[PDB]
Amino acid sequence: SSITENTSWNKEFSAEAVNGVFVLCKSSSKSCATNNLARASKEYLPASTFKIPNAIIGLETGVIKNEHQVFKWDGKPRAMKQWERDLSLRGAIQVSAVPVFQQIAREVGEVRMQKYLKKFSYGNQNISGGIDKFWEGQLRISAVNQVEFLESLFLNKLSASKENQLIVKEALVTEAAPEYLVHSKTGFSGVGTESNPGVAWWVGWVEKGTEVYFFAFNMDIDNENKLPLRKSIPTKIMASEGIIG
Amino acid sequence: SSITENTSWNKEFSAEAVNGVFVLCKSSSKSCATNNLARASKEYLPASTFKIPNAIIGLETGVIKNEHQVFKWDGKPRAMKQWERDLSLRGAIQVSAVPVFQQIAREVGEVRMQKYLKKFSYGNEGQLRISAVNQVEFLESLFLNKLSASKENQLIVKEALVTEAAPEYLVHSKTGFSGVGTESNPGVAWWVGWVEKGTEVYFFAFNMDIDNENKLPLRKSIPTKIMASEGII
C-alpha cells in the first residue's frame, strides 16, 4: 500500500470531538489518503466487521450452503428482538445477528478459521478466549488492513471461490443509486469506559461509474449516542471529494 | 407457472387512463397475480430489457471479460450525452447504453446469440418478442442460477441490476421502452425485476401502452404503488 497523510480531514473530526481515523483509496491501495498515518496502521477489535470474512469462510467451508441459505430461528429467545425470526445472509449481516455468526464460527471450527484468516492476512490473527468470541476478544486489525482485505475481495483475489466472494459482495450492498453501489459494514465493540474506550467502525467500498473507492473508518467511543458519527464523518469526507453524499 | 387474475389493481390502471399489465409472483412463478390474464401472456418487443440476456451472453462467450470490464467510449458522437463516457457493466445497464450493447451483440454474433436465447427460453433482431409472464419465468431462473451460464456470470448480472438498497430488501430491475407509436401501432414501456425482501423473493414484470412520452413515469410508479401497498417496498 501507499498512503498519504492529509491533516485537512481533521476538521470533521475536531468539529465532533471525535478521536479517529479515516482511510480512503481511489482505484487501489497504491493510492490511499488518511488524516492520521499512525492510527491508520494501529490494530483494533473488528467487532461485527468480522462478519465479512466469517461469511466468506462459512460459504467456502460449506457451513453456509449458498446465497439462498436461511438462518432459521429455533424458537428459543435471542437477546435482541431483531434476531428473533428467519434471516437471509444479507439480513444476518445487516442486523449483525450474534447467535447466527457464533454458530457459523462454531461449525467452521478453530483450526479452519485460523487457516483462512492466515490466507486472508486478516489482522494480528489471534482468536483466543473461545471460538464464538474473538472479534470481541484478542483479534485485531487496522484501517489499512481492512482496505487491503476489501480490495482483495473486490478483485476476487482472496483464497476463496469467485462465486462465494461475489455472494458476500452482494450481501454487503447498503445503498444504490444510478451512478454507484455502496458496499459497507458497521462494527461497535461496546462503550468500555471513558478512560479506556470502545471502538466503532464503518468499512466498505464504493463502485462509482468505472471507479472504485475503498474505505475504512474507526473511532474511540464511550457513549452509544456518538454512534451515528461513524457514518456521517466518512460521508462528509467522501461528499467533499465528490464521491457520494 | 400459475397465474391468478385480480380486480384490486384495475383501478390503479384506470385512474391514469392506462392500458397495460402487471404480473407479480411471490416466492416463485407458481404464485403470480395479475390485473390482466390475456395481456400477461402477450408478447412485446423487449427493448432495453433485452440488455439482461445480452449481458449474460456477453459474459458467457468472453466478449465481456468479467465484472470489471470497462466499456470505453471511442470519442464518436452518440445518441445521448450520458453515453459519451467510459461505462461499467452496471453503468451501461442503468442508462440503457444502445451502442455498448450493440457492440456486445455484434462481437457475440447472430447465431450464437440466438442459440443462447433458445436455451434461456427467452421469448419467441427486431423480431424477438416476450411476454410479462415469460419475463418473470426468465428472471426466476436467473435468481435461482438455473440458466445455461456459469453461476458466476449470473451473479455478476444480478448485482449490476441492483437499483434500490434498503436494510430489509434489495430491488433489482430494468426498464425498456421501444418509443412512441401510432394509436394503430403504440409503443410499449417495460419495468421488470425482482425484490429480495428478507428471506422472501418477489418477481415482477410490468408493461403498458404508451403514445405519449409524458406517460413514461407511470411505468415505474404504478408497479411501485402496487408493490408498496402490498408492503414489498
Image (tube, coloured by chain):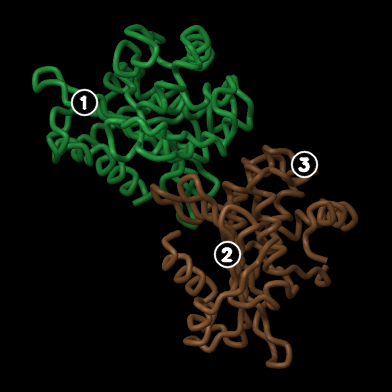
Chain colours: A green, B brown
Compute the Cα span from label 1 to label 2. Answer: 43 Å
The image's mark for residue A190 is: 1
Please report the residue visible at 36 percent of the width from the left and 18 percent of the height from the top: A141
Residue at left offset 54%, top offset 79%: B7
Q: Is residue A164 left or right of residue B170?
A: right
Position in image of residue B110 (x %, y %): 87, 58
Give the CA separation, mark 1 to mark 3: 48 Å
Whether residue A91 is situated above or below residue A43 in the rendered picture: below
Q: Position of residue A124 (x, y in %)?
A: 38, 10
Q: Amino acid at mark 1?
A: Gly
Camera-side residue of A187 and B214: A187
For this view, does B19 lie left or right of residue A136?
right
**In this figure, which residue is indicated by the disc labeled 2?**
B24
Residue A94 or residue A120, whichever sits in front: A94
Query: The C terminus of chain B lies in which quarter of the figure?
Result: bottom left
**Residue A200 shows in this picture:** yes
Across and down, in percent, residue A2 comes to 43, 24
Q: Which residue is mark 3?
A: B62
Q: Indicate the position of residue B209 as horizontal and vertical percent values.
A: 63, 82
The answer to whether mark 1 and mark 2 are in CB contact below 8 A is no
Mark identifier at residue A37: none
How many marks can you see?
A: 3
The answer to which image quadrant residue A160 occupies is: top right
Residue A84 higher or lower than A126, as above or below? below
Q: Amino acid at mark 3?
A: Gly
Q: Amino acid at mark 2?
A: Leu
